[PDB]
Image (cartoon, rainbow, N blue to C red):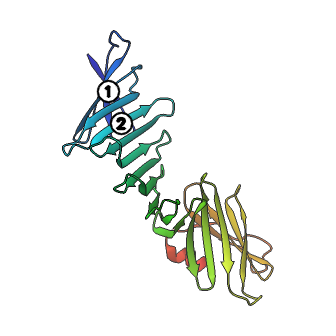
Amino acid sequence: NSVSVDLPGSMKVLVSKSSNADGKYDLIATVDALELSGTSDKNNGSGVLEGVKADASKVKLTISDDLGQTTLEVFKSDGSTLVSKKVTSKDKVLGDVKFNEKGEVSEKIITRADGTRLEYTGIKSDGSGKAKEVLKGYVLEGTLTAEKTTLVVKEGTVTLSKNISKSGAVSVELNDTDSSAATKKTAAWNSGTSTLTITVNSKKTKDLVFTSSNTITVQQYDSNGTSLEGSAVEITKLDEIKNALK
C-alpha cells in the first residue's frame, strides 16, 4: 500500500508503493500535529505536500531530491503571506526564517551542522540587522549588512572583527587605537590557513586560528617573535579571547 521515508528534520513522508494511472505517487506526511498530502513523479519521498493549520494557516512542505533539501513554509490564510520558513539543506544546515506581518523577512537563524548558530534579528529591507554567533562556550555579537556579517570583540583599545561574507567566506581583522609604537597591535589574515597573526613592535606575538570546527585557537610566539612556541590552545570562554587581545 504505502512505504515510509525518513526526512531531514524529524519528519517522515509515507509514499504510495506504486504510481496512479497518471504516473504519480500519493504522498502523506505528518509534521508535528499537521497532516499534509501531495503528489510526486518519484517514489523516493521527494515532492510537494500541503496542509492547513487549526487557525487556517496554510502549510507547504517541499522535498527536493536534486538538492536533498526540505523546505517547510507556513503562510497566512491567503496561502501567500509567509509566517515562517524552515529549510534543512543536504549538509544538515538549518535555516529558520521569521517574517513580519507584511510577509517580509525579519529574523533568520542559521544552525550549522555542528550546532553553532548565526542569529540575525531586526532584519531590515536593506538587508541590515543585528548579528550574533553562538559558539561552544561563548557568543559573539555584531551587525549584519548586505555586504557581510561583522562580529566584534573589544578589549581596551583593540577591536577584533570576524567578518562572514554573503558567500560565507571568513576574514578577520584587528584594529588598535593605541598609538604607542611599543604596544599597538596590528594583524595579518590568511584565509587558506584561517589564521590571524598578531604583531607588536615588529615582533609576532600570537596566531589566532579560526578552525573549520567553528572554534578559535591561540598559539604564542617566543618573546623575540622568531618562532611559535608550545602548541595551540582551543578557546572555551569569551574571557580567553579578550585576554589574547591585551
Residue 238 in the image, given as x and y percentages of width and height: 50, 74
Residue 32 in the image, given as x and y percentages of width and height: 25, 42
Q: Which quadrant, please, contains the N terminus? A: top left
**Closer-to-camera residue (152/246):** 152
The kind of residue tagged 1 is: Gly
- Residue occupied by mark 2: 61
Name which residue lies at 40% across and 52% down. Answer: 97
Name which residue lies at 68% across and 63% down. Answer: 195
Image label count: 2
Question: For residue 151, which quarter of the picture?
Answer: bottom right
| Left or right of residue 181, residue 101 in this image | left
- Residue occupied by mark 1: 38
Question: For residue 177, which quarter of the picture?
Answer: bottom right
The kind of residue tagged 2 is: Leu
**Closer-to-camera residue (228/169):** 169
**In the rendered structure, are the residues bearing label 1 and label 2 in contact, judged by CB atoms less than 8 Å apart?**
yes
| Left or right of residue 194, residue 125 in this image | left
| Left or right of residue 4, residue 140 in this image | right
Residue 48 in the image, given as x and y percentages of width and height: 37, 30
Q: Is label 1 in a helix, a strand or a loop?
A: strand
Report how far apart the C-alphas of labels 1 and 2 lie in the structure: 9 Å
Residue 37 in the image, given as x and y percentages of width and height: 28, 29
Q: Is residue 24 above or below residue 79?
A: above
Q: Is residue 91 above or below residue 110?
A: above
Instruction: State whether residue 246 appears in this view.
Output: no
